[PDB]
Image: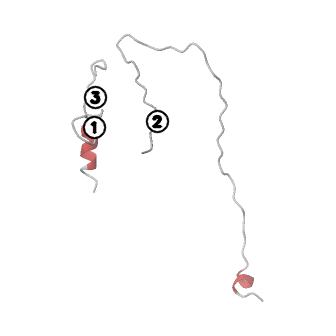
């Protein structure tokens, strides 16, 4: 994931969880009941 | 389980670009409603029929 120097680690999905979502999306599902 | 579509892996690189060589003019369609059936009701005949 070398996209020129931009870090998309918070927008791309994270494979370290069973939901396979991005860290920002993880904050969204834990904010809207 | 419904499939969202076929999987395609774009070969992204630092010095790799894809420039098209040919074109395909396509004609698509889009159906959009514009008007509606103008209706009018009679209060007397509907509620009190004869």
User: What is the C-alpha distance between the residues marked 1 and 2?
Assistant: 21 Å
Query: Which residue sits at x=46%, y=32%?
Result: B6
- Identify the chain of the residue marked 3, using the numbered disc in the image: A
Dot 3, how many residues are within 10 Å of its Cα: few (below 14), some (14-19), or many (20+)? Answer: few
Question: Marks 1 and 3: CB-CB under 8 Å?
Answer: no
| Up-down relation of residue A7 to residue B40 (above or below) | above
| Residue B28 percent location from the top left of the image | 65, 34
Q: Which mark is residue A22?
A: 1
| Up-down relation of residue A10 to residue A25 (above or below) | above
Residue found at the very far left of the displayed protein:
A16
- Depth check, front residue: B31 or A17: A17
Front: mark 2 or 3: 2
Query: Which residue sits at x=66%, y=38%?
Result: B29
Q: Quadrant of residue B10?
A: top left
Query: Which residue sits at x=69%, y=85%?
Result: B47
- Depth check, front residue: B21 or B50: B21
**Screen quadrant of the C terminus of chain B:** bottom right
User: What is the C-alpha distance between the residues marked 2 and 3?
Assistant: 24 Å
Dot 2, how many residues are within 10 Å of its Cα: few (below 14), some (14-19), or many (20+)? Answer: few
- Depth check, front residue: B8 or A24: B8
User: What is the C-alpha distance between the residues marked 1 and 3?
Assistant: 10 Å
Query: Which residue sits at x=28%, y=47%?
Result: A28
| Residue A27 percent location from the top left of the image | 24, 45
- Identify the chain of the residue marked 1, using the numbered disc in the image: A
Query: Circle 3 sits on which residue?
Result: A8
Q: Count how many numbered circles sit on residues in the image.
A: 3
Residue found at the very far top of the displayed protein:
B15
Query: Circle 2 sits on which residue?
Result: B5
């Amino acid at each position: 994931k070398y996209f020129g120097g931009f870090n998309f680690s918070q927008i791309l999905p994270d494979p370290s969880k069973p939901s396979k979502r991005s860290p920002i999306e993880d904050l969204l599902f834990n904010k809207v009941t | 389980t419904m499939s969202l579509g076929a999987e395609n892996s774009v070969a992204y690189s630092n010095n790799s670009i894809a420039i098209p060589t040919n074109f395909t003019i396509s004609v698509t369609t889009e159906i959009l409603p514009v008007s509606m059936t103008k209706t009018s009701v009679d209060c007397t005949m509907y509620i009190c029929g004869d």
